[PDB]
Image (spheres, rainbow, N blue to C red):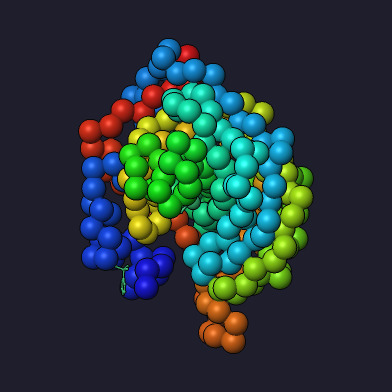
Length: 257
Ligand SMILES: NS(=O)(=O)c1ccccc1
Ligand SMILES: NS(=O)(=O)c1ccccc1
Ligand SMILES: [Zn+2]
């Protein structure tokens, strides 16, 4: 199966997922000087007041926090989006060192990690039907830098010890994903794909310009997770990021002047 190692990492994925070399792959490098302000963007609306988290899962590649998406309770709308997109999960990607870890880059700069808040277009009824559609998903991407602790992250960090290995999960109710956001909603947007197999080309990416700060201790705890399952040789879960892919025939638009 696929992963992030020398043998099964991003440069191998195309053999089983040929869309890896497609026309709208993610992540990309965001060249800030080439991105253009777009006045046709409507204001972005992140409405997570009634978000209902369920469970946190180590899937052998990263960890996922899962949400109950059976009602319109945590939605993203506006910006480049037509209609309403419902939050299903968040996931992170991070590095073995603070100088790398993010998937998107900004003028070639890599951040220490990247958070993805994944939403599906409610016009398609559920996640699996949405990922067959070119506008099925919207992923809100948020960069993490190392500096001050992010208090809203700490409940995640403290639960990781209970999901150290592949296939482990834990209850993760009553977690408020609002505490993971930066102050500003200024963003870049472009059409792209999932960044892990199956690499489906269904995503409107909305990448926030303002990073959040997390502490060195918080990110160190991410790097104590394991890719392997229980009772197997330890392979620390680090560097679970895909590098930037060709921009091809795409334009990155900015929400801000
Ligand atoms: N192409 S892939 O899914 O990364 C893969 C790589 C090596 C062995 C099996 C699968
Ligand atoms: N890492 S990502 O592009 O946001 C993603 C979300 C759901 C499934 C697979 C990948
Ligand atoms: Zn992700």
